[PDB]
Image 1 (cartoon, rainbow, N blue to C red):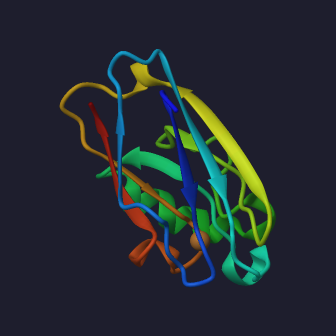
Image 2 (image 1 turned 120 degrees about the vertical axis):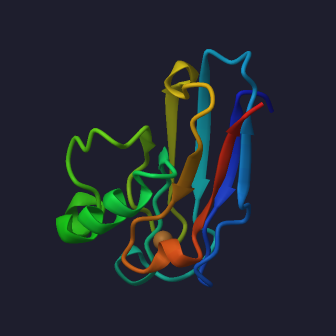
Image 3 (image 1 turned 135 degrees about the vertical axis):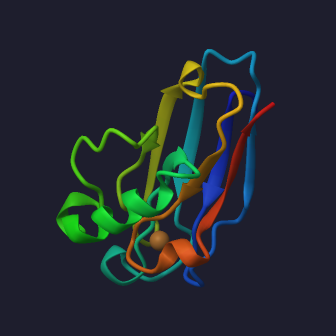
Length: 128
Ligand SMILES: [Cu+]
């Protein structure tokens, strides 16, 4: 592939990767998220959520208060660069966003906002 990445989150509360790079040549970048586990999304749900390193704690916290039916995401949360839905076993979702949204010199994290998962399910995205 190119200007896309495949990410898996499993039954062990892990992303398969902790670091993503995006080609500064890309206008747009795609994240394809899957869940190769057997647990359902209300006990081991995963989403792919991207923000700067410094907004990460805020988005996680309010994502928790927004609740399962809202994908553990605050609706139209302005800190969120890109988000998928919350998925569980056997499910998938992709998200495409404008690379232009990565300003140069910022630092970005991706993570799951299912309560508790970010302690393990987090990783770095960087502009390549
Ligand atoms: Cu998760």
